[PDB]
Image (cartoon, grey):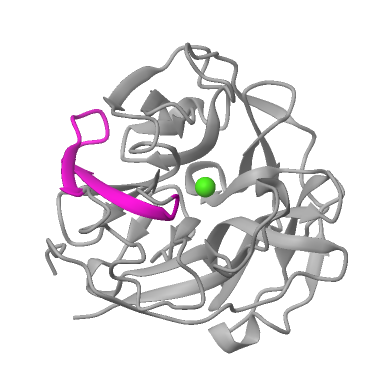
Amino acid sequence: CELPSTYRWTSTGALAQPRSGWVSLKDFTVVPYNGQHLVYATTHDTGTRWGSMNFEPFGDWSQMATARQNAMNSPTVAPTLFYFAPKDIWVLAYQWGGSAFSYRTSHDPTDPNGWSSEQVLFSGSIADSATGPIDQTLIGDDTHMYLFFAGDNGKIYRASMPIGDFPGSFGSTATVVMSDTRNNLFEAPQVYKLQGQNRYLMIVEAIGAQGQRYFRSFTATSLDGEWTPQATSESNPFAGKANSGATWTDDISHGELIRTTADQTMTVDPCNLQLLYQGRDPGSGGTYDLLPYRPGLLTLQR
Ligand SMILES: [Ca+2]
């Protein structure tokens, strides 16, 4: 199932409303867990407070709306969840901790409050960014773990370490692997191994001509290699208003692909791509932090 040069999706509407007290659910990370979906997300309340949560595991996507929403007592904004197989330990990576990126570990990722004390994941800084490093994602191959991240500044960054040294810090240095205008490579990168192909997929969130969010895609044949544009304009995006099949939202924004595995290989099935994204009613206005983001799911047409 080669990636299409022109993507066509169908979509759900919003799959859950935020639990009373939160105005939004955002930045989804999602793994398979004992035949169910296990999702973590960023929260925002009705004032000025960012936080995080998970849902109870749920079997089918109709069950997301009724799955109990569990606030985390330790905020892990824009989280990445995965199982790190070589040490039989679950990892939750995030930002806005004591350094640029942080992680915690657990033996039960369903427990929102069962994560370890905060560990340093990345301690670097980047030039020409108001946010600093944001929206990490991690992926490993046979020999190395990789960290990719953005800076709301048109650049995508990469760090690596031998897989035997993980979990641990990637250090303080990173390599720019792509650069473009701020709007073209904005944030929310996600990197995956394509099942059955010697190819990796990166999707990156962009800001379109009239402010609408959408995803641009790139591929590589090795995680330390160069990235090649795969679907990189608003009119021919990886996923956006042009091809989502969604009218409940114009935005197709910070989310994650459904994976074939929970572990660090971050594998996805190109025969059945599905994107769990955040979207919002186009009639929604007000400040960015209060925007009523909700989860939705795209399914690739083939
Ligand atoms: Ca993310």
Which residues make up the magenta segment? Answer: 211-231
Q: Quadrant of residue 110?
A: bottom right
Q: Position of residue 200 (x, y in %)?
A: 24, 47
Residue at 81 percent across and 62 percent down: it is 22
* Number of numbered markers: 0
Q: Position of residue 221 (x, y in %)?
A: 16, 41
Residue 273 vs 229, above or below: the answer is below
Residue pictured at 15% horizontal, 65% vertical:
6
| 13 lies left or right of 155 | right
Q: Is residue 91 visible?
A: no
Task: Indicate whether 58 appears above or below 28.
Answer: below
Is 223 in the magenta? Answer: yes
At x 63%, y 62%, the residue is 293
Query: Quarter-wise, where is residue 92 in the image?
Result: top right
Q: Relative to residue 228, is residue 272 drawn left or right?
A: right
- Is 105 within the magenta? no
- Front-lying residue, 217 or 263: 217
Choose between 38 and 274: the one closer to the eye. Answer: 274
The spot of residue 198 in percent (x, y) is 15, 49
**Above or below, comparing residue 135 to residue 18 in the picture:** above
Residue at horizontal 58 percent and vertical 21 percent from the top: 130
Q: Position of residue 55 (x, y in %)?
A: 71, 69
Would residue 52 be seen by someone viewing this image from the given angle? yes
Which quadrant is home to the N terminus? Answer: bottom left
Give the position of the C terminus as an image quadrant: bottom left
